[PDB]
Every structure is written in C-alpha cells, then in structure tokens.
Amino acid sequence: FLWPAPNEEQVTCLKMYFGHSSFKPVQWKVIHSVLEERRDNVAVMATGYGKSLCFQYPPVYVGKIGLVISPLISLMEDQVLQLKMSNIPACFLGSAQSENVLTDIKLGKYRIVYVTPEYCSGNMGLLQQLEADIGITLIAVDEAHCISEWGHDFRDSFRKLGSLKTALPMVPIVALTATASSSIREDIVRCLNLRNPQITCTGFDRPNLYLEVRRKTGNILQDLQPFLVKTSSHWEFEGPTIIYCPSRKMTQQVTGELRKLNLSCGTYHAGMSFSTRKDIHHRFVRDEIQCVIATIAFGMGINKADIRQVIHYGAPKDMESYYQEIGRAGRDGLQSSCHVLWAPADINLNRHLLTEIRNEKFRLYKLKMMAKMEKYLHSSRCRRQIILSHFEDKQVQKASLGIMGTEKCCDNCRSRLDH
Ligand SMILES: *[C@@H](CS(C)(=O)=O)[C@@H](NC(=O)c1cnc(C(C)(F)F)nc1Oc1ccccc1)C1CC1
Ligand SMILES: Nc1ncnc2c1ncn2[C@@H]1O[C@H](COP(=O)(O)OP(=O)(O)O)[C@@H](O)[C@H]1O
Ligand code: NA
Ligand SMILES: [Zn+2]
Image (cartoon, rainbow, N blue to C red):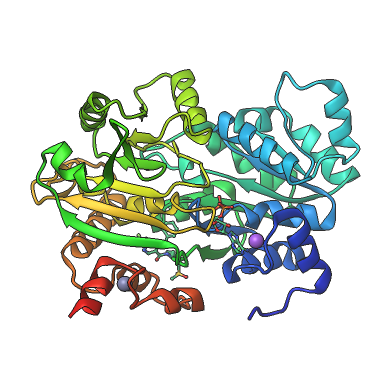
C-alpha cells in the first residue's frame, strides 16, 4: 500500500514503459516528491534494488525531459539501448551528436537525455533553453559520491555541478549515491546546493536471493568444488556466475585455476583497459563467458539480468560493498544464490587500509561498515534479518517476510529447519 496512492494513469504508464505492476514504496517516495513537490532528493540507492525507476519514470510519465548526468559512458550507452527497446526515446548527448538529434532534443522528442558532467557545464545555455521550451522534469546526478575528495572515487568535474541549481532553480535534482556515508551526503548537498532534500534509501527486498556464508580453506579448487560440475569431460558452473575477489592478484589467481579446467571465464578489474573490460562484459551478457572474476571499484559494475550465482571469494570489503555486490544477482527475478567464502586471515578482515584513510569522519564510517560485515560473517541469525536490521526504521516488505524462515532464505534458516 502506497501513500498517497498513485493514480490509474501513473500505474498504466508504469506497466507500459517499465513492465512493473506497482511501484516499490521508496521508488514512489522519490517519484511523487519530484512530480508533485519538485523537491530535491538524495537517493541512497544501489543498482539491483530498483534505483533507475526513480529518475527514469517521472519524465516518461509527464512526457518531458529528464537529464541524467553520469561519468560512465559505456553504461549510459547501454541504458540508451535498453530504454529504446522498452519504447522510451533516449539518447546520449555529447560533442559528436548530430544536429538532427540535437534539434530533436530541443523539440522534446527524447524523454531521457544522458550527458557527462564535463559536457553539462560547458552547455548550460542549452539546458536553460530546454527548461524554457520543453521543461526539465528532473536532473539526476548519478554516481554523486564522486563529488567527495575522500570518497575513493573523486571526479572533480562533479564539483562543477553546483552551477545546475543557479541556472535551473525550479528543476529538482535527484543525486544518487551508493554509500550511506553521512559525510559524503552532506558534501553532495552542499556542493550541489540542494534545498531541504528528501533523503531515501533502497532496502533489502530481494526474496529471490539465497544467502550463505561458509569458511574458506584458501585452496581455490577445493573451495570452488561444490559449485563445479563435470559434464561431457568439461567443467562448468551451474549458471552464469560472478566471483568477487578482494584483490586484483586474487582475481588473477582464481581465473588461472578455472582456466586450467577449460572453464569459460574472464577477469574484470580496474587495471584492465576500458576496451578489454567492455569486451568481457559484453561477452558475459551474451553468455559467451560463463563466469566473470571481478574486483569491483570506482563504479565498475556488472549488469546482466540472469546472474544465477554470486561468490565472494574472501571476506567482502564491508557491509555496503557486500550489499551492492549481491544486488547484482537475480535481476530477472528467478532463484539465485550468493555465497561468501571467508577466513579470519582475509585482508578485508585485517584492514590497516582503513587505518591509513585520511578523512576522519569517513574513516569512522568505513570502520563501522567493516564491523557490520564481521558481525554478519560470524552470526547464527537469519542472514536476511541481519541485512534488514541495518535499515532500522524501514518497513520489511511482505515478500521478504514470506521468504524468511524457509529453506530458500539463507543457510541459517536452513539449519534451523533441519533440527
Ligand atoms: C537510509 C535507509 S533508512 C533505514 O530509511 O534510513 C539509510 N541507510 C542506511 O542506514 C544503511 C545502513 N546499512 C546499510 C548496509 C547495507 F550497509 F548495511 N545500507 C544502508 O543504506 C544504503 C547504503 C548503500 C546503498 C543503499 C542503501 C541512509 C543513512 C540515511
Ligand atoms: N517497481 C517494481 N516492481 C517490481 N519489481 C521491480 C520494480 N522495480 C525494480 N524491480 C526489480 O528490482 C530489480 C532491480 O531493478 P533493475 O531494473 O534490474 O535495476 P536498477 O536497480 O538499476 O533499477 C529487478 O529484479 C527488477 O525487476
Ligand atoms: Na513485471
Ligand atoms: Zn534466513
């Protein structure tokens, strides 16, 4: 149940352009705030939990323009393709765009326009014309935590986006961050000059993720044996699989062992060229590769709808990273599994890489997130209950209540059902 209720036209539009029958409560909280109150928002949201509807839906519903600012060009191009397949006109606007498309943007032919921050600052006159002639429903600043010098993903062009509010005072900004850090949120608010923004978060309503934690020996094939099946003289996983490793070195070691089994896999980390990463990601989406072994940072992400298995090979960096990374599994809604294989000696459990972080408020935050991860690894409680417990106030959705306690929820619920 949603308050205030979406009207029938809003629901029909949701069905027709996004294929969803109802809004998630937090999606509606952002959407309604933008449409009715023209309110700035800081949306603490992760891919895989329903992030994109919050900024793609409003311009589609009113038939106007939504501007999405992001530094991740390849991801923006993929979104343009997906939107066009869902019959939503969208484009990437850059220096190379044809005048026919640029005039089409001015005529309001496109609902969603993706731009880089750097383009955005050099063409503010264009944005004001768009607002005057057509109306900008919202500006979404994706990867907004890149504004912060200490957030390990600093991109200085984001700090120029303070000009948006001055040029377009009546246009709400939705700043999307995948960290709940208060110091980063406060910097986002002040740098962008947001006004009394609404703060929201995705939660953990992902009932199709089975969660398991088990101890790791550190012998790679022994640890990976339960996930591997030999079929016709060939080793394979049961389905498309991501293995997240804490270090690039571990990613290469794991990949090396799997290649000796003639397994179809690819590595994915920030040391690789962009062109090679793009190829690996495309091959995984098209099922030419079965397993990606990744060390995720800097807004690298793996976007594939039918990821059946996620394996954290070693303790995750912290509780937010873990939440981000399991969220990438099972986006088609079918059953998926997320396993953590960990050991006390794991480097993310022996982090002096925090004892070196410069910013004091941020270091306290990361220490807190690491403590949460450690408590989770050691717990006998329902893993889903633990994750949800970190969203103190937040309502638990019915589907999550229904899965908890059953054999498909987590390893600890399964153990309870056995005895
Ligand atoms: C917003 C959610 S709420 C309960 O409505 O205030 C809030 N988020 C969190 O407190 C929060 C806590 N813990 C975790 C996690 C997964 F690390 F355990 N996530 C989390 O949140 C998010 C963090 C990253 C991405 C999405 C959500 C904000 C502080 C106000
Ligand atoms: N309003 C909704 N109703 C039902 N399921 C939803 C809704 N919004 C998102 N989802 C589901 O949540 C998951 C995450 O959304 P998805 O579109 O894959 O990515 P993103 O989080 O980047 O928007 C998917 O499984 C998707 O089907
Ligand atoms: Na659906
Ligand atoms: Zn459980």
